[PDB]
Each structure stands twice: as structure tokens, then as C-alpha cells.
Length: 147
Image (tube, rainbow, N blue to C red; front, side):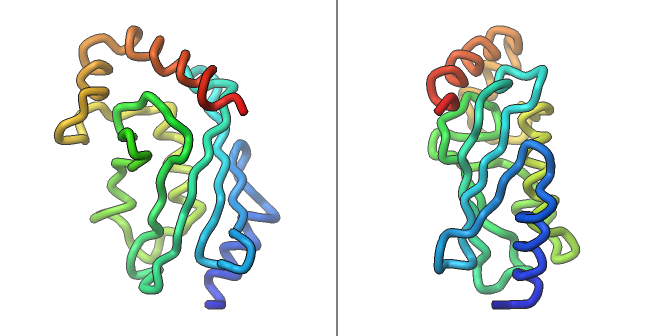
């Protein structure tokens, strides 16, 4: 195991950020199961979101790959759980780390950016009527993120 991955793994296990848990899949040190609590003050409040994360072999030069497993109505997260976030793509750098990515995802849940995706119908709904799109997000939260 790369010493950096050991370090990151221990820090996340021992000092997780509030509302975030990240634990490796047994015998697969590069894969993690993540739980992020929906932030207070959002339609995701009360919900818990499952994500998975993989460290590819060219980490940390290349970013971790991360996706939602729980269904969610959010302008930056698509139907397949794919997260539109710049630090997971061209603003990644090896000076960032897994913890930074998880805090950013957690904050994305409070601060959606409805202009980033190229063609998201969900994003269009949030742009046209944010309070209305939040109804849908709040009912999905109740249905899908309450387990």
C-alpha cells in the first residue's frame, strides 16, 4: 500500500469530517464506501447519501473517481450518480486529497451550481424555479436517502 494512501485512510477513519464517513472495501484498499449526510437547511436534510470512490493506479497525479450511489435531484449530479465538479477533473491537483474532495461534495449539496453541466434537464429546473426543484429534491430525499 502506498504510504500516502495509508495516511489518508487512517485520517478519514480516525478524524472524519462531521457528516462524512469513508471506509475501504475489504481487501481492496483503493476502493471506499462513503456516506455523506444531507446538510441542514437543504432539501437533503435528514437523508444519508451513499457514494463510492476509487483511487486509480496513477493517483495522486490523477484524481480519485467518485460517484453517488443514492438517487438524488441535484443540478450537478446526473441519473447515473456522476458528479460535475472541477476538482474531480481539470482542477484536480496532487496537492489536494480525498478529504478535500469529500468536503467539496458535501458543500456541493448546499451550494449547487446550475450553470456547470452542458445539458442537464435537472439543472434547467433549478435555474427556472429553484424553490420548486427543491420540492422534488426533498421528496426524493425522503424516498431514496432514508435507509
